Structures are given as C-alpha cells and as structure tokens.
Image: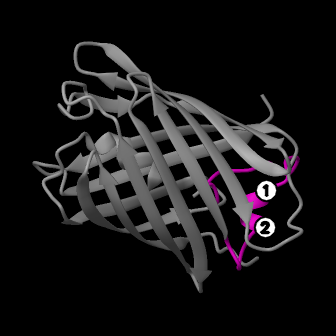
C-alpha cells in the first residue's frame, strides 16, 4: 500500500577498497511485486577503478523480490519508515568486505545510503587484476539468528579461464520500526547481471531478478 507497482531508486555509495577511495551515484527504477529492478551507475570520484567492478554490484534492496502470499514479506512491511542491512563478504583468497545500506522512502522513491569497505585483496589476484566475468545465479537462505533476520549465500564469481572465485555472504536485515514481525525461514533466488558498460566501468547498467520461495 505504501509501495507502488513502479518505484524510482536513488543511491550514493562511498567507499574504499585496498586503500582506493571512490564515490558512485545510482539512478534506477523497479517493480517491487515482480522482483525486478535496474539501475544506471556513474563513478563520480576515484575512476577509473583499479579493481573488478563486480565485487560492488550486490551492494547496489530485498524489497525488489517477488514474495508469495504464504511467506511474510519483512521488507515491504518495513515501509514507509524503511530498514537497514549490513553484509560481510569473505572471499576464498583472504579478501574481505563489509557493506551497509540505510534505505528510506519519500513518495515514489527509495533513497539508499551505501558504504563499502574492502581490504586484503592480493595484488596478483583476480579482483585487483580485473579478471572477473560475472556472478552465477544464487539462492539466499533466510532464517532468524538471535532475533535478527539473517541471509546466507554461497556466491561464485566466474573468472576468465573458466575458474570460479568463491565468496560467502552473510547479511543481517533490520526494520527501523520496532515490532515489524519476523518471517519464517525461506529462500530468495537471485540473478544479477551487468547489462552494459563503458571502457573502464565508469558507467554501468545493472539488473536483478529475485523470487522468494519455500524450497
């Protein structure tokens, strides 16, 4: 009821990876009930980025997921006040990232305040050498841990030379308003894709389709 079938999205990300500082703006639209969104991104400071753009893409909102009637939708029930999430990303060669997003809504627009910090990526590894191609489609497991809604996903970045580079996500999600009821455990399938880009990934168009289910 707060959430319309078509919503606009505004975003700013600030961050630092291996010491490199950057600022990225996003402008997008999506369909919350169909689980589809896309976004145009533009690096404003720090470009051309010296690391694989792909590590950032899942930090650029689980409101855009199709939920069936039989699973409580914690994210759509969080609005208009909104919610926040914090994520750790643990890569198999020791790279580590922490990201957060604080999401608010004004009228027909979501605003996103995103922070992304990464460290310990080996200078000779696929992230700093820009050898990544895409994330594989994934399944996030949603459950409650110590009273907090938690999503785990085992992610894989396809690399040049048909190898995958693995990363474990853990995200915690918290409604701003007390007493939004927690859902039962469930799954969210995701597919995220870079649809287009320019030479050094200073301008990128991103898309995600996500669908909640019970297994």
Q: Are marks 2 and 1 in contact (CB under 8 Å)?
A: yes
Instruction: Quadrant for the N terminus, please.
Output: bottom right
Residue 51 higher or lower than 35, as above or below:
above
What residue did someone put label 1 on?
Answer: 73
User: From this viewpoint, is residue 205 visible?
Assistant: yes
The stretch drawn in magenta includes residue 164: no
Tell me what residue is drawn at x 85 percent, y 53 percent. Answer: 72
Q: Nearer the viewer, residue 31 or 116?
A: 116
- Residue 80 vs residue 115, the one in the foreground: 115
Residue 79 inside the magenta-drawn segment = yes
User: In terms of depth relative to the viewer, which is nearer, 50 or 202?
Assistant: 50
Position of residue 195 relative to residue 214, above or below, is below
Tell me where the magenta segment starts and ends, as one range.
62-82
Please name the residue that numbered disc 2 is placed on.
77
Residue 113 as seen in the image, left or right of residue 177: left
Q: Quadrant of residue 177?
A: bottom right
* Residue 207 pos. (x, y %): 42, 50
Q: Residue at x 25, y 39 (%)?
A: 52
The residue sitting at 20% across, 30% down in the picture is 123
Give the distance between the C-alpha atoms of the residues marked 2 and 1, in whole angstroms.
Answer: 6 Å
Q: Position of residue 85 (x, y in %)?
A: 62, 57
């Amino acid at each position: 009821s707060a959430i319309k079938p078509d919503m606009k999205i505004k975003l700013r990300m600030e961050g630092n990876v291996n010491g490199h500082h950057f600022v990225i703006d996003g402008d997008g639209t999506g369909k919350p009930f169909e689980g589809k969104q896309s976004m145009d991104l533009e690096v404003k400071e720090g470009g051309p980025l010296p690391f694989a753009f792909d590590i950032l893409t899942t930090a650029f909102n689980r409101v855009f997921a199709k939920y069936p009637d039989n699973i409580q939708d914690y994210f759509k029930q969080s609005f208009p006040k909104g919610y926040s999430w914090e994520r750790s990303l643990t890569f198999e060669d020791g790279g580590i990232c922490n990201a957060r997003n604080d999401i608010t809504m004004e009228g027909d627009t979501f605003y996103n305040k995103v922070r992304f910090y990464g460290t310990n990526f080996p200078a000779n590894g696929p992230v700093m050498q820009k050898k990544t191609l895409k994330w594989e489609p994934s399944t996030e497991k949603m459950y409650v841990r110590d009273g907090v809604l938690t999503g785990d996903v085992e992610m894989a970045l396809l690399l040049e030379g048909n190898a995958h580079y693995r990363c474990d996500f853990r995200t915690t999600y918290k409604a701003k308003e007390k007493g939004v009821k927690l859902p039962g455990a469930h799954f969210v399938d995701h597919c995220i894709e870079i649809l287009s880009h320019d030479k050094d990934y200073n301008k990128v168009k991103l898309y995600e389709h996500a669908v909640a289910h019970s297994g």
